[PDB]
Image (tube, rainbow, N blue to C red; front, side, top):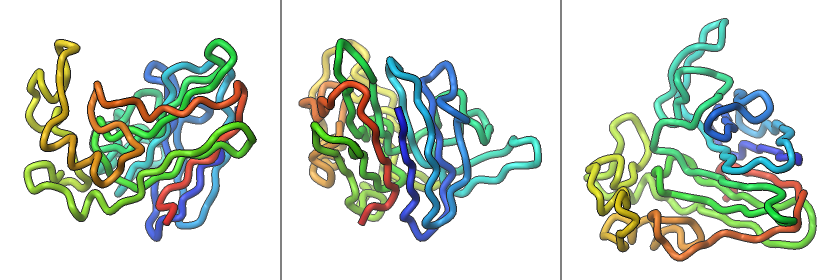
Length: 206
């Protein structure tokens, strides 16, 4: 499957792609304002994620640090990123279909649109100014808007017991972005697409 990652932000972002225990394609790359990077994700990839990283610094070996979404200090991510990170999530070729969604469960750092470039389904988007409107207690000093689990580490926010309900904090993310997961047990906003669809992830779509 092909995923065209486009940075429409006025600032540079370092795209990242991983399935948790391995990188997807090269795993990461710098995307200056306006640049597009197309990656190939193997069919059947389950639990894949694409996200943007901001304010990064990498040496010649590809090692460094990012203020948001840092993945073990690597340019080419092999693991998931450090919150806050707006997440484009997907599982491909799952019994004949693809499943995609955007999640704020791990916070929000950069606005994003995640849409198919092929026929059969609609896209999802979370482009509201979540960082600007972020509740004071969730603001990340390093940049972005943290999710409540990251900040408070409670069973309720992290849904540790598999039993949790919406909260003042999750409702904030849901109000600004109704089409993205605001907490673990949020009413699903997952989109079903034809198996083997292709996609485009656009940072700062509006």
